[PDB]
Amino acid sequence: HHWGYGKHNGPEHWHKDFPIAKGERQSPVDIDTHTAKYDPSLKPLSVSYDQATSLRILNNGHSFQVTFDDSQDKAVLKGGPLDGTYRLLQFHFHWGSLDGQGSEHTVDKKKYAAELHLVHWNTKYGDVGKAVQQPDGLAVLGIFLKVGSAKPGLQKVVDVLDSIKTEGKSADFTNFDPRGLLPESLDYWTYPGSLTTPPLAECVTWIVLKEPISVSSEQVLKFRKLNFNGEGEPEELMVDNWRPAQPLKNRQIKASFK
Ligand SMILES: NS(=O)(=O)OC1CCN(S(=O)(=O)[C@H]2O[C@H](CO)[C@H](O)[C@H](O)[C@H]2O)CC1
Ligand SMILES: [Zn+2]
Image (cartoon, rainbow, N blue to C red):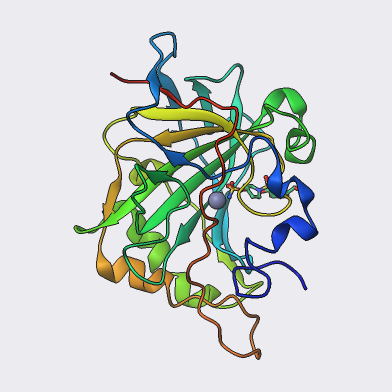
């Protein structure tokens, strides 16, 4: 039917409605750390989030997302492998039913408990709808989550999740600072890829940070209380909303660090 993460509408089915699922630059991928090549020509990442304006938090039926005002150059990603300025639009997560899975990218086949995606679009294309039609339209900053100590910066997010339990629910979510979700190091891998959900458009420069953030078991367990379903429908926990690693094909993963 309409796509999802279940047995009958999961990642293995997506190619039927979205044939680009089997394309030449699909995401996520396994990051083979010994094969990634250090590229000394990569500029450092510029993450400028000091003026970020969060608007709302939303259960969109496949994850939850915090949305930002992208009508001007407030929160932007620059440098690294990127040319030009990319505006922060939203962030969301992918996570598992258990701590041993949940991430979309993997590192030497290692799966993390979850993965955070900060989604930015290239301002030269004017709006995100136009950007997703371009090979360099989007830049997604991917951050791994492992389970251990709590991430204080994440707690304001986890505390309102019970108010957006089911598909379509949203809440005001102002004055959230996404800087509290970043690890210490901005060391990264980068490769050309795609959206990891339908329409799987091949429009993304992926920037995946080497250093995971630690979140607590209690924080992740609140992720797993969300529902795929709308209210009044049979309750199906929002867990394992991750696409597995896709063939690397004719691509090279570059590292910003030795
Ligand atoms: N998981 S992922 O790799 O981060 O995938 C993306 C990230 C962001 N989108 S999205 O396609 O760019 C984008 O598309 C729309 C316009 O088509 C919307 O208005 C969304 O606001 C927006 O996220 C959906 C999925
Ligand atoms: Zn994502």
